[PDB]
């Protein structure tokens, strides 16, 4: 806990992998909110 | 009444206190440093209060243009028409020489997350889309971890910070285009189209992402918003000259002894910034040739101007250049200035979207000429032709990339014309 | 060699096999759910990058599948792939070496980095090694201008390089180890090399500077 | 009623809100130069040839896309407006191929005509030119795409009129190429109409290739009988022979399109 300014604490990214970013977005899905709807399945509908 | 000297910002007055990554970037550490503090009270005070404090701060966008932020963010403050409203955070960080936003995202992510909410509450937004360049994969992952932490702790999501306001923060990654930093092009990339800018009108606050009111903001502009609201705008205005108020992250690169990223008070003298933090120029100030103050898209300035120029929006304009992203590139007398500037034109050639004519063809045309200027295979009368070609690309383009490829060429012709002519004549003698 | 037209080959044709894996379909469903209903086309870029991560490059079949699942015209997917430079429409090596040659990195002798890699790997810029491990290309500013010279290999930045170091990074990659991202000089990030000139004092705790009411 | 008042070179014209600078200049008889704007297609604002000066404003605005605002005075013949046109035309012609003698669009080309009226008389481009591959999109349309000026009229027509989204842009910058990326045929009952909208010789009629020149053809206004729509047409005849069929505009029938069978 004593103030140490001599270490690089952002060392987690040395372990990240190819699918990391999308896996975390999958885990974040439950926390979202109902998206808004235009009223049509697509502009081509 | 007046501060006639600027610089020497005390660490307690600095905003990005983990800029160098020497503390924890997760929620626990950031909460110690003051983030996510009384954020419930900020949100309940109201959109008008948040905008009013941002207006008083004199804050201007750190993305390049430097438009007054509070006025810009107040376009969105209007009754809903039925469409949603979004905040878009520009983390594309594409301007050569500029690396400020990479640190904020990876070492102080929760400042950005909190700014989205405070900025979003002011605009009335229902969510934030943080557009981060695709090469910032590790930085993007760090932000998602932070966003997950805030989602789990109630800081963002349904009834965020106990304020009754529902706000979601998404992260979308680009796929490799400097032009996607442009606010309208960024919107179109999110929508799933080629990163080609739009024409204005319509302005993004009326028709934006998904055809809904939207506001595009820089990472640094958003990250400082929570701090402005707690500590107060007058604090942020206490620093800097009038109308150039605030503190600015600077990136000093090029021929310097200690290239670095650093936060300093706006309107700081340029010579002080380089000599103090970056270790001065390689070989000393007398070996300095020219400086690019605000990244590639800013005219260079020669040593004669670098001595006494303050690094704020207004002063650099009176020098016929711009603060831009406040990214300082330093070239020494050993540099081949023409080759350096030509490579920037070659960069704008590879990053133009091709949508509109003056930049689709003009930037190619400038690239080809500047390549000949390097070898000297040109006549002295082509220099003035290049100037007119540049002025035909400026003001006649959809975005500002063309404006940003003309100003660099205009700077070289303005301050280093004798160097161009000297190289031309030498090539003539050799071809005898 | 910078071609933006497709000519069918035995390896790349609309019938070349490719479909997402069962795990990646769940990832897609998350991607598509991040955008408003009626604008699934917004998922084209993230889903396209997903295909390249699974397969290593984007064959013509891969683009068509992305369009089919998102109900997007196939051409509109072809446009996106060509516009953006991170999408590989030709096979690339297991490790994709990218060198920034823009002015800030050019002023700090990024050319020396480019020359060292060329000597060690025995390839010229744009070519692939015979073993298909490495592919070399020049790129523009990668966002690490202060830490120049720098290169990106796959999704990791290796910074503050020197001709010796980049050979070491290649040597580790050849053996099987994956080197450690970050500046290879005596520093950690963007901080002033010799020593910190700011943020040396302890950070101020919560509630510091708060205004009267807030 | 809801009409607002604007000035075109000082002469007052009353225009409905939402009207563009361009459309306002029409009501006084002035045609702004154009390459990308088409009244029956979506606005694009990419050629930049419509640029026009607004008095007491420092930036030229794209007339095809900018709505008029009350009180604006539109300077169509100002020096700033005329110099903007010359610059744009100079960029358009920089990489354009020297193909007018071998190009069927000669004599009816908007690039030729608008260069003569709104452009300079000489070039200062001392560099090499771009060259592009040719793309086969069927037996009815010939593609010499080195002549393309990237106006995206074909892309918009196919999407917004024909309903076919097979034409697009691949690449970016000077290397951006209109096409299908893949080897595909733009076959449709309205395919031929991309030939007309294309203001240059990039898209031309294969059947009509090389047979005639615009000035030597007599124009006869007749009707189409291949169907019951009664599309109005023009029959181009030279020396007692029929050379081509062109659409003739009728708003209440065929607008300015005809079917491939008619053509
Ligand atoms: C070619 C081009 C690239 C740009 N890149 C960025 C960028 O990377 N980051 C950024 O914040 N703004 C960038 N901008 C500026 C944006 O268009 C826009 O003005 C800005 O993001 C608004 O944010 P602000 O109000 O906080 O300054 C770019 C503009 C252009 C023309
Ligand atoms: S100026 Fe260049 S980058 Fe901007 S819209 Fe025109 S072609 Fe695209
Ligand atoms: S399109 Fe027009 S300018 Fe171009 S070669 Fe054909 S006739 Fe000449
Ligand atoms: S082919 Fe013709 S219509 Fe299509 S973009 Fe080129 S010039 Fe315009
Ligand atoms: S100039 Fe190379 S990373 Fe920016
Ligand atoms: S007619 Fe307006 S930009 Fe083309
Ligand atoms: K044509």
Image (cartoon, coloured by chain):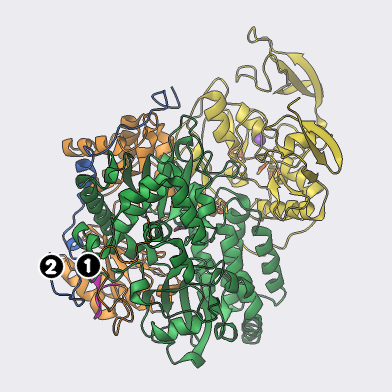
Q: Position of residue C45 (x, y in %)?
A: 36, 43
Q: Which residue is mark 2?
A: C175
Which one is nearer the viewer's eye here, B140 or C64?
B140
Quarter of the image with the N terminus of chain B in it: bottom right
Q: Which residue is mark 1?
A: C181
The magenta stretch spans which residues?
C182-189
Label 2, residues with CA under 10 Å away: few <14, some 14-19, many ≥20? few
Determine whether, in the image, residue C43 is placed left or right of residue D100: left
Label 1, residues with CA under 10 Å away: few <14, some 14-19, many ≥20? some
Write down the colour of chain C.
Answer: orange
Q: Main secondary structure of the magenta part?
A: loop
Whether residue D173 is visible to the viewer of this picture, yes or no, is yes
Chain letter for the green colouring in the rendering = B
Determine whether, in the image, residue A7 is placed left or right of residue B91: left
Whether residue C59 is visible to the viewer of this picture, yes or no, is no
Residue B27 is a magenta residue: no
Whether residue B411 is situated above or below residue B165 in the rendered picture: below
Which one is nearer the viewer's eye here, D48 or B367?
D48
Chain letter for the blue colouring in the rendering = A
Secondary structure, mark 2, is helix
């Amino acid at each position: 806990e004593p103030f140490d300014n001599t270490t690089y604490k952002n060392l987690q990214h040395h372990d990240y992998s190819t699918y990391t970013f999308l896996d975390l977005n999958l885990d974040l899905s439950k926390f979202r909110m109902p998206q808004p709807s235009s009223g049509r399945e697509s502009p081509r509908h | 009444p007046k501060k006639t000297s600027f610089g020497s910002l005390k660490d307690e007055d600095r905003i990005f206190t983990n800029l160098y990554g020497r503390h924890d970037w997760r929620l626990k550490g950031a909460q110690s440093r003051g983030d996510w503090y009384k954020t419930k009270e900020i949100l309940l005070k109201g959109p008008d209060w948040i905008l009013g404090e941002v207006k008083t701060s004199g804050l201007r966008g750190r993305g390049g243009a430097g438009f007054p932020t509070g006025l810009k963010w107040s376009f969105m403050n209007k009754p809903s028409d039925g469409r949603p409203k979004y905040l878009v955070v520009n983390a594309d960080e594409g301007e050569p020489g500029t690396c400020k936003d990479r640190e904020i995202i990876r070492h102080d992510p929760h400042k950005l997350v909190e700014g989205c909410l405070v900025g979003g509450r002011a605009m009335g937004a229902r969510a934030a889309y943080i557009y981060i360049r695709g090469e910032f994969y590790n930085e993007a992952s760090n932000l998602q971890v932070a966003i997950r932490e805030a989602y789990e702790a109630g800081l963002i999501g349904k009834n965020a910070c106990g304020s009754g306001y529902d706000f979601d923060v998404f992260v979308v990654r680009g796929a490799g285009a400097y032009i996607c930093g442009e606010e309208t092009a960024l919107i179109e990339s999110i929508e799933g189209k080629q990163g080609k800018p739009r024409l204005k009108p319509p302005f993004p606050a009326d028709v934006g992402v998904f055809g809904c009111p939207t506001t595009v903001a820089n990472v640094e502009t958003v990250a400082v918003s929570p701090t402005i609201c707690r500590r107060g705008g007058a604090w942020f205005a206490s620093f800097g000259r009038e109308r150039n108020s605030g503190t600015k992250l600077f990136n000093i690169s090029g021929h310097v002894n200690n290239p670095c990223t650093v936060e300093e008070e706006m309107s700081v003298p340029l010579k002080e910034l380089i000599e103090k933090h970056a270790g001065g120029v390689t070989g000393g100030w007398d070996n300095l040739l020219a400086v690019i103050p605000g990244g590639s898209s800013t005219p260079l300035i020669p040593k004669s101007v670098c001595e006494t120029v303050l690094m704020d929006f207004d002063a650099l304009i009176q020098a016929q250049t711009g603060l831009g992203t406040a990214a300082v590139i330093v070239m020494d007398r050993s540099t081949d200035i023409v080759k350096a500037i030509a490579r920037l034109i070659e960069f704008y050639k590879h990053e133009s979207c091709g949508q509109c004519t003056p930049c689709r063809e003009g930037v190619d045309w400038m690239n080809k000429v500047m390549a000949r200027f390097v070898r000297g295979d040109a006549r002295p009368a082509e220099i003035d032709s290049l100037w007119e070609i540049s002025k035909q690309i400026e003001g006649h383009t959809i975005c500002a990339l063309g404006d940003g490829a003309a100003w660099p060429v205009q700077g070289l012709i303005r301050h280093f014309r004798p160097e161009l002519e000297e190289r031309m004549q030498q090539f003539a003698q050799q071809h005898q | 060699g910078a071609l933006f037209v497709h000519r069918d080959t035995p390896e790349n044709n609309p019938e070349t096999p490719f479909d997402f894996t069962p795990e990646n379909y769940k990832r897609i469903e998350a991607i598509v759910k991040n955008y408003p209903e009626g604008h699934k086309a917004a998922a084209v870029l993230p889903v396209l990058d997903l295909a390249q991560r699974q397969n290593g490059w984007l064959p013509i079949s891969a683009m068509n599948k992305v369009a089919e699942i998102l109900q997007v015209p196939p051409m509109r997917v072809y446009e996106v792939a060509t516009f953006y430079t991170m999408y590989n429409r030709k096979p690339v090596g297991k490790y994709h070496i990218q060198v920034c040659t823009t002015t800030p990195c050019m002023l700090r002798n990024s050319d020396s980095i480019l020359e060292a890699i060329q000597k060690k790997l025995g390839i010229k810029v744009g070519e692939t090694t015979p073993d298909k491990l490495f592919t070399l290309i020049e790129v523009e500013c990668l966002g690490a201008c202060v830490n120049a010279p720098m290169v990106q290999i796959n999704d990791n930045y290796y910074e503050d390089l020197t001709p010796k170091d980049i050979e070491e990074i290649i040597d580790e990659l050849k053996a099987g180890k994956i080197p450690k991202p970050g500046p290879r000089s005596g520093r950690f990030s963007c901080e002033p090399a010799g020593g910190l000139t700011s943020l040396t004092e302890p950070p101020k705790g919560p509630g510091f500077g708060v205004q009267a009411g807030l | 009623s809801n009409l607002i008042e604007v000035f075109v070179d000082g002469q007052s014209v009353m225009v409905e809100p939402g009207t563009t600078v361009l459309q306002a200049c029409e009501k006084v008889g002035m045609q702004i130069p154009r390459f990308c704007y088409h009244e029956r297609l979506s606005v694009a604002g990419n050629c930049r040839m419509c640029l026009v000066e607004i008095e007491k404003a420092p930036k030229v605005v794209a007339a095809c896309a900018m709505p008029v605002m009350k009180g604006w005075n539109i300077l169509t013949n100002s020096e700033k407006t005329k110099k903007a046109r010359e610059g744009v035309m100079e960029f358009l012609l920089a990489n354009h191929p020297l193909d007018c003698p071998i190009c069927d669009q000669g004599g009816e080309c908007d690039l030729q005509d608008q260069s003569m009226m709104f452009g300079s008389d000489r070039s200062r481009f001392l560099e090499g030119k771009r060259a592009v591959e040719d793309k086969n999109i069927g037996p009815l349309v010939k593609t010499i795409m080195t002549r393309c000026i990237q106006c995206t009229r074909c892309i918009r027509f196919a999407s917004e009129i024909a309903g076919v989204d097979d034409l697009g842009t691949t690449g970016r910058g000077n290397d951006m190429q209109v096409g299908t990326y893949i080897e595909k045929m733009f076959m449709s009952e309205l395919s031929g109409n991309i030939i007309d909208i294309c203001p240059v010789g990039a898209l031309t009629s294969k059947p009509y290739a090389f047979t005639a020149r615009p000035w030597e053809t007599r124009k006869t206004e007749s009707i189409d009988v291949m169907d019951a729509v009664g599309s109005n047409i023009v029959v181009s005849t030279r020396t007692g022979e029929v050379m081509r069929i062109l659409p003739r505009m009728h708003e209440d029938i065929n607008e300015e399109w005809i079917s491939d069978k008619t053509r």
